[PDB]
Amino acid sequence: IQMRPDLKGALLSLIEYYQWDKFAYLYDSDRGLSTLQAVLDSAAEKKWQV
Amino acid sequence: IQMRPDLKGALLSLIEYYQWDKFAYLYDSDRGLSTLQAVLDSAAEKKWQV
Image (tube, rainbow over all chains, first blue to last red):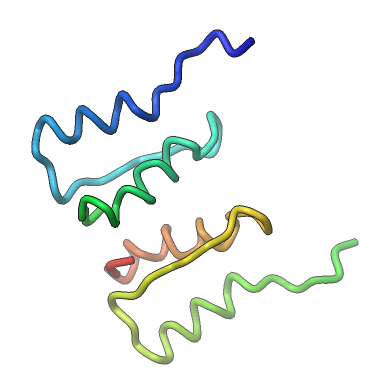
């Protein structure tokens, strides 16, 4: 019973609102890279230079 | 006692050999992401577009 909501989708919509294209993604090897894969897989569909 | 040698240094030295600057890194989550962290952390040290 994962009480925490899936944050992957939330952050993906915010970067789309500000219309970013070239940023830096500082990640810690702690909470998992599930939010890192989500933006790395989407780094090809919507182009980004992350 | 890990029999398999570390590949992280080897691949980085070959990419530096072919002198690549923009490539595609198709990784599978199966064998881990230790090599994925090696290219991502070295993506900034040499300024690549992965």
